[PDB]
Length: 60
Length: 20
Image (tube, rainbow over all chains, first blue to last red):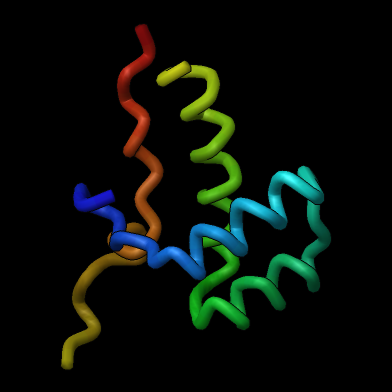
């Protein structure tokens, strides 16, 4: 992703990918933790997960 | 070295605009 949003690294993408694939849903604290670990905001995780769904639906 | 960017610059939600 080199449009608008910052290009996520492999490590970042892999973690978010595995977490979402493993646990389609997360808790507030867990999301905050994941975000904290990624040195980002909860929004980064919240939107990434949703972006994946929207990508599946729209850009099927 | 700046705090401009945007609250949605780091987290954009329009990467998937192609509905089709």
